[PDB]
Every structure is written in C-alpha cells, then in structure tokens.
Length: 171
Length: 171
Image 1: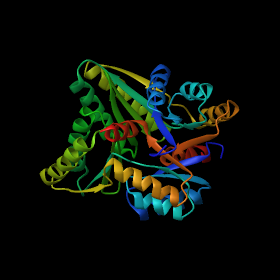
Image 2: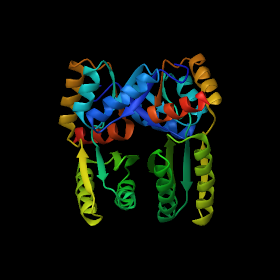
Image 3: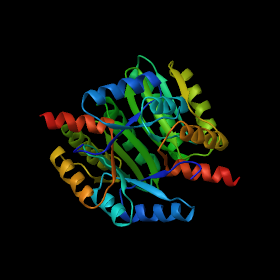
Image 4: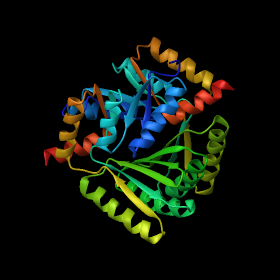
C-alpha cells in the first residue's frame, strides 16, 4: 500500500489478534506481521496465512487488569521504573480494562524478579495480573524451529532481546 | 540464524544506529531492520545496505536528557499517563543520560499537545528534551515513496499508527 508493505499487529490473546486482523483487512490491509510473547498466537498467525512474525524470545508480556485505571497506572509505573533501571525496553498500551506491558532486554533472572514484582503490585493495588510468554534460551530456539516447520518465512527479534539470548547461550 | 532471520534496531540518532549495527554484526548478526521516527536514519540504513525499515508515520520520539534519572522518570511518567489515556502505544528505554519515548496511535493534534507537554515537563524537572520525527499524513506518504526510490524492499507500519494515518487520509 501507499503507507507501507506490512502492518505490525501486537497480541497477548489469540482471539484479540484475529479481531485486529479482521478490522485491518476490512480497511484494505494486506500483509500483517504478528508480534507476540505467546508462541501459540504466532502459530495461529501462520495457520491463518501470515508468514512474518516478531518474537519475544527472552522477555515477557505483563497485563494488569482492573476497573480503576489510576490503580493500573500506579502498578505499571513501579514496573516501568524497575524494568528501565535494569536496562529493559518496555512497551505499554491500554485495551479496555487491560494495561499491557511488553518487556525485553533483561536477563532471565531479572525477568523472573519483575514477574514476582508484578504479582506483589497487583495485590498491593487490588488488581489482577497475567503473564504471557517468558522462557529460557533453549525453549526460544525450539519454538523458532517449530515456527519455521509451520511455514514462517521471516522471524524478527528485537536487538536487545537477541543480545540477552546470545549472552545466555554463551553461558 | 538459529534465533531468527532479522534483528530490529531502534534509533533516534544516525551515529548511534551505525554503532548498534556494528556491535550486532561483530556478534554475527546478518539482516537488520532499522526502526526510526527520523526518515534520514531510515535513508542511512538503506545507504549502508539494509532494505527492511519500520516507520513512525503519524507519531514521534521524545527524548528527555539529564544527569538525574529520578527527574527523567518523573517527566516520562507524566508523558506515559497522558499518552496512554489518549490511546497511545508508548515504548521507553534508557541510553546513558537519555530516556527515549516512542509514541504511536494518537491523532496529529494530540501528538502536538504531547510534544508541548514534553517541553513543559522538561522545564518543570530541570532537564532537556528533543523531538525526533512528527509530521502529517502527506509527508508520511512522500517519505515512504522516497524510501522505495532509495531501494527499500519491506516497509512495516505499527497497526495503531497505520489506523491513525488512514483516519487522517479520509479527512
């Protein structure tokens, strides 16, 4: 199209991913790359005819959920400060009662610490939290090979995510 | 490679982009997609042999700079709350004394408001701020065509960015 070749659709839920693709296809979108921490969502993207994927190999998605946006923001702000200080790249967006946080570029131990901190903040601010993705480098390698077997043509990795995974592989 | 085909490198400075590419190439990285709000950085990516680009068509990058990280975080947190409430996707990362904020998925008027708010917060917290990118839909279309003339093979747009730009084109 006039604005580009590929739209990037981010998802942490397979049904929300399919809803977003349908909206964009109705607006005349053609090629769609799906970005997700959930390997199953990337597999669904391939099943439905996508072949460009963006992974979260070493990181995870944290989703705070609640009626009170000010409570979600208080929890997210503590996650932002801690994650940034450890050298993370963090992406935030609102979707109804969800505040979605995609985290990359921290070692596995630090990400597990952040996941535990998310659970503590959820309890502190009277909200719920879900984790999407979060695995080790061997699982990342295994799941990338599965995506290729299922017909992925282009798999993209955030450079900070890749550098963390390469460091984990050397160890 | 074993972890994927493409690394995504984000940049708001052309020299930092080239530094990151060299680091990754030394670690054995091959294909690199460059993501930037600055069309000149995307043009440099093509000049140096890249052909995959990720734009920020309707959004912008805001960079707070200062010695006091707690001051940068105070300014960034006000930007996060305001941008999220308007329906933005925001990506944050630290790089030395810079706090980088990539904003997509808000209409042009709201983005201009956020840019003015960034200038006010910089003054309030005794830090500096720079804007990278930020243009209208006609400029976006013009610059995408220039990237294609300069040999771009795949141009990706965030779906929220694309939906804002499509809405601006209908108007």
